[PDB]
Image (spheres, coloured by chain):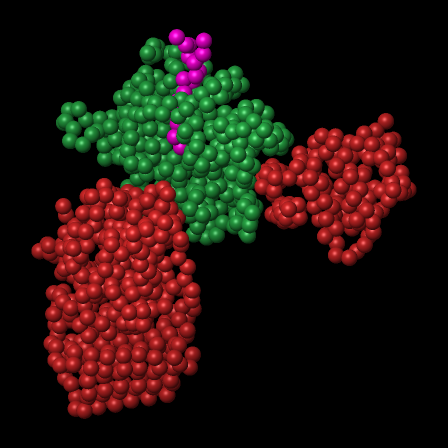
Amino acid sequence: PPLQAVLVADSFDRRFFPISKDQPRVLLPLANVALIDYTLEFLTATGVQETFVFCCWKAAQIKEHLLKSKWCRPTSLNVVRIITSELYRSLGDVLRDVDAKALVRSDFLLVYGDVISNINITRALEEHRLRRKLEKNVSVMTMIFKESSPSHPTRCHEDNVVVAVDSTTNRVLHFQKTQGLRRFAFPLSLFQGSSDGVEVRYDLLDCHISICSPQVAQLFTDNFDYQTRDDFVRGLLVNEEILGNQIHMHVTAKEYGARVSNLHMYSAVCADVIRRWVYPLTPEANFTDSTTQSCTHSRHNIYRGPEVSLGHGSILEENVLLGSGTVIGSNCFITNSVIGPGCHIGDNVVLDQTYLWQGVRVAAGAQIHQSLLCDNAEVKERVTLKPRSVLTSQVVVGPNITLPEGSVISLHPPDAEEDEDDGEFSDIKVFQNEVLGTLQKGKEENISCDNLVLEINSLKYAYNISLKEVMQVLSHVVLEFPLQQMDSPLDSSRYCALLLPLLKAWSPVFRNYIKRAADHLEALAAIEDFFLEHEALGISMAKVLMAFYQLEILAGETILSWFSQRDKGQQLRKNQQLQRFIQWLKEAEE
Amino acid sequence: LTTLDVTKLTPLSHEVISRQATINIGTIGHVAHGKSTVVKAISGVHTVRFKNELERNITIKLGYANAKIYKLNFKLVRHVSFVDCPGHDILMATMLNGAAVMDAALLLIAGNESCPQPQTSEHLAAIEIHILILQNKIDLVKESQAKEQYEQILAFVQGTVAEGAPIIPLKYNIEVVCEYIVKKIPVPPRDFTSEPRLIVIRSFDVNKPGCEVDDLKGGVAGGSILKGVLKVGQEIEVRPGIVSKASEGKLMCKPKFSKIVSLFAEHNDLQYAAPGGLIGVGTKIDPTLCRADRMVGQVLGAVGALPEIFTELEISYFLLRRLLGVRTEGDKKAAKVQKLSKNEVLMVNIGSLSTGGRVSAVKADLGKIVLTNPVCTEVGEKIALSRRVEKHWRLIGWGQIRRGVTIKPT
């Protein structure tokens, strides 16, 4: 069987800003070579036969970058399939377009477009194939990790991954990240599901070369909520009672594999490529066929291109790469840095862990430490730079202007920190509260009567209260809403004005709640208790009695039975306003 | 054996000449994988077996089980297709999305306790709609079942305050429940004169591995008929069709027309096919175009259905405040449906078509959801909107489709 692979050449995280606003993050040079060429060289060193490159943002630039490469030649053993569409914006969307196109056949590879690796995974591929052959397509994904230390500068705190796997058959049981977590919690069902062996691993750097079955594309077409890889694994590990699909794991201890996510991963992977940690993928080896990147390797990992014309007094002590045509002046001191092709360096300059790309121009007396200089840049004289300073796409830094530690300059104002120029200067209680909140939401959002009645029925089914108790709670909420409409007026006019439109709008829910004569008597008793609790607006207590007979809430016979039934409530109902309302109801009835 | 034929002009829902699929009956209760055993005890364990494959969408698809309820060498008049869905929220979203769905709701309640699963089932039955309460906790004590029947009678009093007037408290109780369902549930009115619309729910492949070159059957799809009558030999009309994005832009949906070669149900069905059951149609389609659950979500029309393939649908955003009857003892902001945020996935269940879509834009009563796959139901149908709360797709709201971006390639 052939070995297929998919390559997500568009990282959908907004991390390389505003670096990815000009050229994408898969076209940035580590050491004069884009990460697309590194990942494709890793794929041909693996032994794949056909790839599927997926790129959405600036995909024409990626296409014109990789068509002139070694992998688009007809003599290449590993062909590529450029697929261009601006519709997808997620890795799950990429995999569901793979499922809709039906490109892969069996056991295809999954890789991002910014993964630097040299691992031969034929052993892991045969392990995944035998695990699929014995257990009858139960194993679906084989994640790959590298043995690393938690204190290593490669893995940062934003991308640290802690897993909990099995010891004898290396299947993954738990998988999470440490993004702002001082204490980690692991589930308890992993021990009951596997009583043979379990091990928690924090020494695993993620390389995102997780080979997998074509069933992950089916699972991505089923679950549309799975956006990327990690939430897909976190949802597959918790949904084990249905569609089990155990994920296995492979570890690498003698080969290198990582990716980039920010400036820290970029700096660490660049320092590892310069220090030959990803051998055979080496800058002087020239794995891609290009005359502008041919190099030679001296001692102390010094990489020298053609036509440098090095000056007197310049010191290159450790981990220095020089591009083709890079002009270097006198009395320089370069260490742990990569320089692009066609650059111009001044005099009495220091370069400490910097990353200079093609076309830059550094004047004399400049102090640059741990920075990143992008294409066609210009740097004037008498300037001191601090660590973690980024300048993208021809940013000129004026003389006698030092930058702070956190400082990113570009041509876009709101994405970067600034823009530069030739000058750098510019029980029943909870149910009652839920019913009151539902009534407040229906009054604020102007909900209909049917949805309000459905929400009231859902709250009555959830609280499991009786019908008369739910009617009394609804009457208490309707009496408390007009009592909460006024803060401390202590008057009947504002309470009547708040209770008239509330009873006029919510008349259908009050008719659906209070329907029988016993429900009408319970509503009359709740109205009497609310008038006893709100006696300061008691002059409106008859005004509600003329309202419930007007909106067909309380009938005239029920009102007569409530007035005839007697105490404090009988003395409150024997007022002049209640007697006048009863006389008006008897005159209007007949 | 049956004695059906291809000579029919205007059939009825209670016609005894077909005896394959007369009426449908929904089942939503507090089963927790207990309703399949009740459907096997009522109809049959290995009765529904036509074409099996790998379970792709278990919680999203609903299974239909036919039952020929006979009476008196017995005589069969009408058959009931019990629709069992994994999770009551999917069945509720399928029922509250139009008409002619879940005509006879069966409330499979438990006589053990009064937990919140029966309250959520009663809320789903109230949001869907003829109820049919049935206690499954057999083999109990006399006074214990009497107290459980008193608690179920209080729950049924609250039900009768909403919609609650069935009465039913191992084979004899199942036969009594079948007789009560045959005597109580009336025949629902179905439109047979309209065009046949077969919404696919589960597609299968009838071609075995290593088959002959001449004996090759492809495109044995299966779904549910909304309205009309489907006969063998009629040219079907796949409304979604093949959706291809090979033009480097908007995907074109080419409708693939295939003549219906046979209508193969769970039993030996005839040429004519009516609604209210798991209708399986084997047409003259390719095996690659109709793979295992690949042609799902496609409206297999018959006379050129008006519903076009919509990519972005602007509907009326109307979400509920809390969950329908789902509230535990804690309830620490669990039953609280949030607002429609930007770039959020939602499972719009337009009838039987459950398609995922991202919330591209929302203005205060109008949400424009961009669907992943092309859907073709109607221009103003009642579309639901669900959201996965905790590893389970639960309904969050409903709405009406106000506008849509249609596309029809050829």
Q: Is B66 covered by the magenta stretch?
A: yes
Magenta-colored segment: predominant secondary structure: strand
What x and y, as percent, mark residue A76? 11, 56
Q: Chain B: what color? A: green
Asked whether the viewer can see residue B276, the reply is no
Q: Please tell me in which quadrant of the rendered image residue B152 appears.
A: top right
Residue farthest toward the right in the current orientation of the protein: A576
**Which quarter of the figure is the C terminus of chain A placed in?**
top right
Q: Nearer the viewer, residue A407 or B346?
A: B346
Figure chain in red = A
Viewer-closest of A428 and A487: A428
Residue at image location 38% in from the left, 84% down from the top: A402
> In the displayed structure, does residue A76 sit left or right of residue B1?
left
Q: Is B83 on the left or on the right of A112, as rendered?
A: right
Q: Is residue A575 magenta?
A: no
User: Can you tell which quarter of the image residue A22 is in?
Assistant: bottom left
Q: Residue at x 39, y 57 (%)?
A: A186
Pick whichever, B40 or A349, lies toward us. B40
x 21%, y 45%: residue: A132
Magenta-drawn segment: B62-79
Q: Give left or right: position of A61 versus A581.
A: left
The answer, for residue A318, to whether it is visible in the render is yes
| Residue A333 rendering spot, x and y as whole percentages | 23, 87
Q: Position of residue A160 (x, y in %)?
A: 34, 65
Above-or-below relation of A367 to A92: below
